[PDB]
Image (cartoon, rainbow, N blue to C red):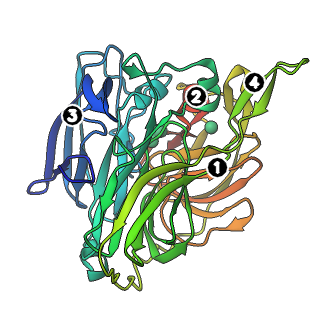
Amino acid sequence: GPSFPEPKVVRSQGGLLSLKLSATPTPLAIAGQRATLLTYGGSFPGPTLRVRPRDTVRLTLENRLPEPTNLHWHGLPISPKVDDPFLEIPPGESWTYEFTVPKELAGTFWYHPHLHGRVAPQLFAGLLGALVVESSLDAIPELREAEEHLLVLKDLALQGGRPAPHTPMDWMNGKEGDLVLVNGALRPTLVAQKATLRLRLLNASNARYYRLALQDHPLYLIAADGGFLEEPLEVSELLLAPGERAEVLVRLRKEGRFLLQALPYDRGAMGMMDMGGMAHAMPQGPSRPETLLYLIAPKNPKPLPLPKALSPFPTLPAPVVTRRLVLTEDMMAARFFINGQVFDHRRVDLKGQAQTVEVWEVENQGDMDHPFHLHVHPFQVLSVGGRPFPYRAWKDVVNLKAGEVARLLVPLREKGRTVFHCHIVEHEDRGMMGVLEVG
Ligand SMILES: [Cu+2]
Ligand SMILES: [Cu+2]
Ligand SMILES: [Cu+2]
Ligand SMILES: [O-]
């Protein structure tokens, strides 16, 4: 096959993407070994669904797992009557998700389980895939002539040829694995044929962070989680927290081999030590550096000019309400809270009005990073930690380091009951989630 492994793509046909997937235990070859993973469509990652605005998606999920499951269409601004976080598909049963792709939408999205209490083990075991919304913007020469690839960043740990079980410490920290993979492959080689690459990046890990840096090169950020920036933004590195997506252009500067690395990053994970008094909690510190892939540049590379502009960001109405949400931890109990409470599916926490805009101030009073996610209603990050955000784009996950406040502009779109939660999915399973009702 191609030197660079990417998931199989399924495209809409005549404006319709009609597909049956089964969530199933699946024997595979993974990183040179044989293992049984939980997969959609018999692959890890699952197939990439590629659609255009106004397409109809009709996806029948058959549950062939021994436990209930469901889907979350992460990042899609569709109705929570479709993207229903409370729905349970029992073992052996099927459910059809049907929705229309919104008109004003572009970018990289993804699908994964969201059955409360069961997300972390199901996602860890391999249940994920990408969804790409194509854009008329993809036709501009500076993007059309770039070489495009999807990078699904997901780590894994295996024990006895199956995903490693969660330990108590894993429920506290979020589980990370020693196999740090791209598209389910261990350190693949990308032999570029063009001097400009357009990389769509997805962090589909439970808890691992990727502080991305390409040796000797900057990255040009052109999209965040849920849409394009207004113009490319040059960055030296790019942190991708769990659940986040980005698209970057890479302009290869000379012939050679360049490592794409996940550089050391301390997200505040904890360990335990006993030094004669003790036992107490002690910081794990930064992650060890990882090589993600080897990027080979072509001969005499002459990158395309960057796009001068991408997509203008919508002018939003003045906001009608300010919310303040506070995240806290009880680490030794592996319990996690929003405004002092754990999730209760019967309890509505926030009530808002459709087609109004809210300001959400999300404050991390814990010591760990927490990547905050809101379903259904993409937001504009205004500032984090008191620093203004350097671009305007739609996001649906925002990382908060210890002590930081994120200020979000949140237009409320579809009516109904939905959720917001930490996307370290162990923390969501352990209570860090709340309910928003839009009417
Ligand atoms: Cu998600
Ligand atoms: Cu968290
Ligand atoms: Cu969710
Ligand atoms: O989620």
Question: Which residue is outermost to the right?
Answer: 277
Can residue 307 be seen from the camera position used here?
Answer: yes
Q: Distance between the residues labelled 2 and 4?
A: 35 Å
User: Is 62 on the left-hand or right-hand side of 153?
Assistant: left
Kindly identify which residue carries mark 3: 41
Disc 3 residue type (three-letter):
Gly
- 98 and 415: which one is in front? 98
Q: Are marks 1 and 4 in contact (CB under 8 Å)?
A: no
Q: Position of residue 87 (x, y in %)?
A: 37, 27
Q: Position of residue 188 (x, y in %)?
A: 34, 50
Q: Residue 68 carries which label?
A: none
User: Is 186 on the left-hand or right-hand side of 344?
Assistant: left
Disc 1 residue type (three-letter):
Tyr
Q: Where is residue 240 in the image (x, y as percent from the top left)?
A: 53, 53
- Residue at image x 29%, y 65%? 148
Kindly identify which residue carries mark 4: 272
Q: Does the residue labelled 3 lie within 8 Å of ligand 1?
A: no
As helix, strand or loop, the secondary structure at mark 2 comes to loop
Can residue 339 be seen from the camera position used here?
Answer: no
Kindly identify which residue carries mark 2: 347
**Which label's residue is closer to the chain start, 1 or 4?**
1
- Residue at image x 58%, y 35%? 434
Q: Do the residues labelled 2 and 1 touch (CB within 8 Å)?
A: no
Disc 2 residue type (three-letter):
Arg
Q: Which mark is residue 265?
A: 1
